[PDB]
Amino acid sequence: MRCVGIGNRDFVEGLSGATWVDVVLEHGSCVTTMAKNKPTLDIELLKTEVTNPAVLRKLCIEAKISNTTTDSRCPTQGEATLVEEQDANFVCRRTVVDRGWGNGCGLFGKGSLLTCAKFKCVTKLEGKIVQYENLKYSVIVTVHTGDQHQVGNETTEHGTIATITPQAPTSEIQLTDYGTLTLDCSPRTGEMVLLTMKEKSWLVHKQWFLDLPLPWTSGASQETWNRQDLLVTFKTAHAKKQEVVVLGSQEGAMHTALTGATEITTTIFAGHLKCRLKMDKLTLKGMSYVMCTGSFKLEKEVAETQHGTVLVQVKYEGTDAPCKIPFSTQDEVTQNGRLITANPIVTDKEKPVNIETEPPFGESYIIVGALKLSWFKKG
Amino acid sequence: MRCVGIGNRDFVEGATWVDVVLEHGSCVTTMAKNKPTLDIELLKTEVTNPAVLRKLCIEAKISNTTTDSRCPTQGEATLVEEQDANFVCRRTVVDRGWGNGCGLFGKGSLLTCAKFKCVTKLEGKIVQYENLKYSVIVTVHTGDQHQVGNETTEHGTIATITPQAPTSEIQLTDYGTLTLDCSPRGLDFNEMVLLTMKEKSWLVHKQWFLDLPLPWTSGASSQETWNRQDLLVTFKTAHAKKQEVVVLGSQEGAMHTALTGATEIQTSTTTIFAGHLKCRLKMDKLTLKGMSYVMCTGSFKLEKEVAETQHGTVLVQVKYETDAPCKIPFSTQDVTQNGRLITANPIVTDKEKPVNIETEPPFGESYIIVGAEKALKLSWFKK
Ligand SMILES: *[C@@H]1O[C@H](CO[C@@H]2O[C@@H](C)[C@@H](O)[C@@H](O)[C@@H]2O)[C@@H](O)[C@H](O)[C@H]1NC(C)=O
Ligand SMILES: *[C@@H]1O[C@H](CO)[C@@H](O)[C@H](O)[C@H]1NC(C)=O
Ligand SMILES: *[C@@H]1O[C@H](CO)[C@@H](O)[C@H](O)[C@H]1NC(C)=O
């Protein structure tokens, strides 16, 4: 058993004599799928993964400067030129300053001032385009066996995991002791970027990532940083020097901006997808088993889940293992309407068996064997 | 002779008092007959010692993470750390059942607290209109070779202006006393805030500073109680008993990027950008030195090639031969003998020390009368 007590839990019941069942999967939402004469299953979308993500850009967040060079001109002696202006690694700025006899020139006017610095990036993040072909959803399917350990165990070694990609959207999953289940999935959009920055991971929109005010480089191999002035600015000290100043690490700014995005290659908060379960090859274990004639004992007290279902963990006298569990629900006096666990069986005498049921509204009794459990499901 | 060759330069012309407007970056040249011409600039404005409106925190660290969890129908989770102000906390609800250690199915409370302590912060000081000190430099048009455009070393004299003593008497050596009545009058008195951050300083608006997304404390100096700590510490919830803390990190670069739009004030508590200031110069005590001096009779010669300033004026730097001291004769001829001078009394205090003279040449092919009879003449095509 799985997904019990999960807040976002949908109950999808298959139609009579339906070999298949439609299901909708989102992360944090699990679906309990039951079909007549077929095992009740719990389907959850465990995790999505993006493999071999293509590199879209590379933004710089922390920059450093060096080899500060400067050229200065007297008025009408040209405009200051430097060879560093020709280098893409260097960021530069020209300005005009008041020149006269006070600052070394013989003429009064506007003198040119060029300053270049050596733009190097020490710490940088990464943006990766995720293509539709590179998705790989992992869906866990857990059969309602009834073992005492797997109620909401949340472990992966209970059910079976199927990987589904847009390249291979359909897959046959072999559930042990229950056969083969075909799963036809149709993934939709889920144009978005994965921003690996200094060991973390985020998933943001493409436009939001491209409009980031950060120096960037294309994802192809000379590391020419565009819009370098976003990290390095130029303060005019006086007519013979324009000093460089660096803004510093924009990490904290990026964390502040990414607070709104969805955190995490494994990406949780998987996308909505619509899938179909063909169960023609699924086998319900214990269809053939004889009924139990022994007297049961309540191992664990009955508990009502969030959806009005109650779950019963019982134990057995023996002398009849294995067997089908005779389960019935009386009201107010009536007989059975609905059992969540498809086939309640006793694999071992010593192993308690869990069984989930939907009792009717108002006072009712749950008979197993003969054990009668009173219950009051608030109208 | 300060203020020469500075781009944004105003000329105010004359009795015994002149009205002037002072702006950082701008400067004025004041002239009056029988009174020495001066160069007045609003140097820098200093906030005396302002009061902290708000400290903000830009970097944060977390320790002593504590967590409490309760089963459904077992009440809300409680912690003694919720009583402490140093701890930032967050409470959530998680799905609980037989799978995560509870006997009942439902929503269980989960409370998590973390010790908020902060390594590096920035302060913000409200600049009350009272605690100001305008520094106004006044430089005399002497003509010495030292002060040609000397921004290198201060040569003039500076006056202090406060809203309590807006009037000041300054003594110009060999030139008497100058009375100065400025009116600060005033930038929305409590609008600006000085933002002291890790040795640097900025001036920003009050609303822009208050709307900054950063934790804040009352500015008084230990036991800093931080409000709005969630802006630097978030909580992610691992499943069913644990809520891990995430620190946003150093917001230094965020602050630098946000302050790129504001005007950097270059020093820690002095502002090298002032703002407008309306002043009145009273010269009833100002002495024009050189009015009893003799006319120069020797022949001059040009020390430095005539230079034109950006305002159309001409600067001429000459060396004298011998009365020493004496007054340099000066006027301009196109035909027209009249010529407007910027330097009021060009005198030669010493023979060796050259003398600079500023004049306003008339439009076109003028001539100059430095000297006498063998006084040198220079051509100038003012275009
Ligand atoms: C979760 O389950 C663990 C063991 O898993 C299952 O154990 C039995 C029921 C077998 O059916 C085996 O195939 C499974 O792997 C337990 O050790 C553990 O205590 C369980 N935890 C909780 C909270 O129920
Ligand atoms: C660059 O600066 C280093 C020291 O910072 C110096 O040793 C080197 O000679 C400089 N070279 C150039 C080309 O500027
Ligand atoms: C400016 O003042 C300094 C200080 O003595 C002086 O040495 C220099 O000659 C002056 N004139 C300049 C730099 O043009």
Image (tube, coloured by chain):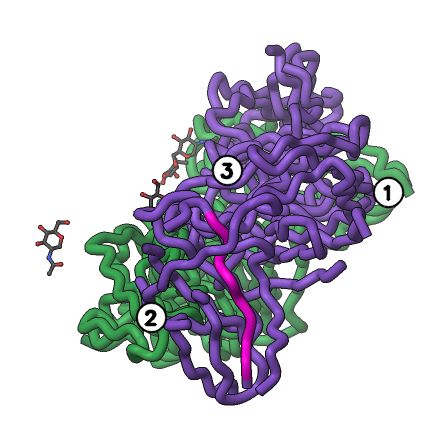
Chain colours: A green, B purple
Report the side of B282 relative to A190 (left or right).
Answer: right
Judge whether residue B117 can be spotted in this image.
yes
- Which of the two residues, A173 or B120, is positioned nearer the viewer here? B120
Mark 1 surroundings within 10 Å by alpha-carbon count, few (fewer than 14), some (14 through 19), many (20 or more): some
Judge whether residue A118 can be spotted in this image.
no
Disc 3 versus disc 1: nearer the observer? 3
Q: Chain of mark 3?
A: B
Magenta stretch: includes residue B330: yes
Res B271 → quadrant: top right
Which residue in the structure is indicated by mark 1? A331
Mark 2 surroundings within 10 Å by alpha-carbon count, few (fewer than 14), some (14 through 19), many (20 or more): few
Q: CA distance from mark 2 to mark 3?
A: 38 Å
Where ligand 2 lies, by quadrant? Answer: bottom left
Image coordinates for residue B318, horizontal then vertical, percent: 37, 61
Mark 3 surroundings within 10 Å by alpha-carbon count, few (fewer than 14), some (14 through 19), many (20 or more): some
Q: Main secondary structure of the magenta part?
A: loop
Q: Which residues are magenta?
A: B326-333
- Which of the two residues, B191 or A299, is positioned nearer the viewer here? B191
Q: Secondary structure beneath disc 2?
A: strand
Which residue in the structure is indicated by mark 2? B305
Which residue in the structure is indicated by mark 3? B267
Q: Secondary structure beneath disc 1?
A: strand
Image coordinates for residue B279, horizontal then vertical, percent: 77, 46
Which mark is first along the chain, 3 or 2? 3
Image coordinates for residue A315, horizontal then vertical, percent: 54, 28
Magenta stretch: includes residue B285: no
